Amino acid sequence: GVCACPRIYMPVCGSNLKTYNNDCLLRCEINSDLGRANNLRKIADQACDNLTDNVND
């Protein structure tokens, strides 16, 4: 479906470790085919670059 978003800048982090410029964009992708296929959900209310994980630490 067509899903598009006003230009709010408030970065968030998906479970794919990609930073989205706002929640609207992340939620568009949560519902996309690419999103469902990766069980995409939000993991942080900030850019991913503020987080680390067990792979890169």
Image (tube, helix red, strand yellow):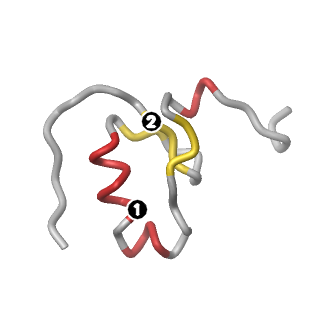
**Residue at 38% across, 75% down:** 33
Query: Residue 56 at what x, y percent from top left?
Result: 80, 37
**Residue at 34% across, 27% down:** 10
Q: Quadrant of residue 49?
A: top right
Q: Secondary structure at mark 1?
A: helix
Query: Residue 54 at what x, y percent from top left?
Result: 85, 41
- Does residue 37 sit above or below 50 in this rendering? below
Crowding at mark 1 (Cα within 10 Å: few <14, some 14-19, many 20+): many
Q: Contact (CB < 8 A) between labels 1 and 2?
A: no
How many callouts does the rendering have?
Answer: 2
Real-space Cα separation, disc 1 to disc 2, in angstroms: 13 Å
Where's the C terminus, which quadrant? top right
- Does residue 54 sit above or below 46 in this rendering? below
Left or right of 28 on screen, residue 40: right
Query: Residue 1 at what x, y percent from top left?
Result: 19, 73
Left or right of 54 on screen, residue 4: left
**Residue at 28% across, 26% down:** 9
Please name the amino acid that badge 2 sits on: Val
In this rendered view, identify the residue nearer to me: 56 or 9: 9
Left or right of 50 on screen, residue 8: left
Q: Quadrant of residue 29?
A: bottom left
In the picture of the structure, the residue carrying the numbered disc 1 is: 30
Among the two numbered marks 1 and 2 on one chain, the one whose residue lies closer to the N terminus: 2
- Does residue 42 sit above or below 35 in this rendering? above
Q: Which mark is residue 12?
A: 2
Please name the amino acid that badge 1 sits on: Ile
**Residue at 44% across, 67% down:** 35
Q: Which mark is residue 57?
A: none
Q: Secondary structure at mark 2?
A: strand
Left or right of 45 on screen, residue 26: left
In this rendered view, identify the residue nearer to me: 41 or 52: 41
Crowding at mark 2 (Cα within 10 Å: few <14, some 14-19, many 20+): many
